[PDB]
Amino acid sequence: MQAVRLFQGYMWHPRALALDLKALLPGEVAGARLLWDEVPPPTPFFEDGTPTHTQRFYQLTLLVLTEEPPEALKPLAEEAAEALGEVLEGLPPEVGWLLLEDLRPL
Amino acid sequence: MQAVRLFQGYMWHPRALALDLKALLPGEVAGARLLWDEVPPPTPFFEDGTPTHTQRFYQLTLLVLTEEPPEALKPLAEEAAEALGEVLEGLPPEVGWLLLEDLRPL
Image (cartoon, rainbow over all chains, first blue to last red; front, side, top):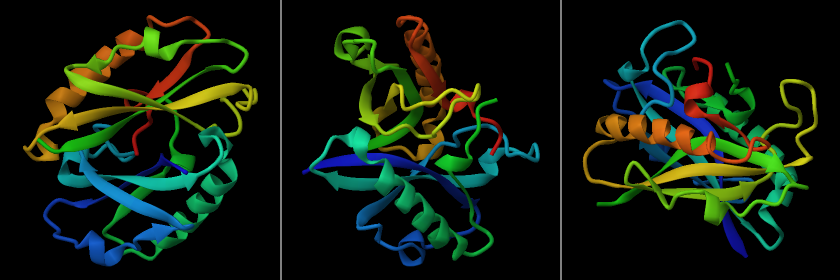
């Protein structure tokens, strides 16, 4: 059983807002450990042209255990993405977020 | 000195194309450890409508050992992202990629 870290997307909130993510988020999604780590903003601006430095960003990762090759995880990845989306919809409106499925190349 | 895994983006190449990444990719970038891990296609189709199931995908990550706040690692992220771009442009032309700099504003 190898542990595969699958990037899920990003979530963020105003840096002046001291949210307790450990109390707001579940420890797991689709049987996999949900991890989040504070990181520098992935891009300098939001879609509306405002700077990303005003927010604290977190990288979302699902730690998936599998006995099969990592490249065969799509079924679980899709299920986890849907479930994580539902989880994030339950967070306060002050929390912004965008999952892998909604990221776009310029 | 703790480590933070900074997701940098994706790299991919035809499954039919053999590539020894360990011999082509540098051990580090900007002094930071560069990691590559195979994962399922992050999306079913490329922008040009062609299928992604014909390619092998890898998550690119930078393992950063530091103590300072994440919102201070921006400089490293900058040169790392720049160096990583240079590295990828050095690989065979069949190799494709999408880094954080290629993302549209969130």
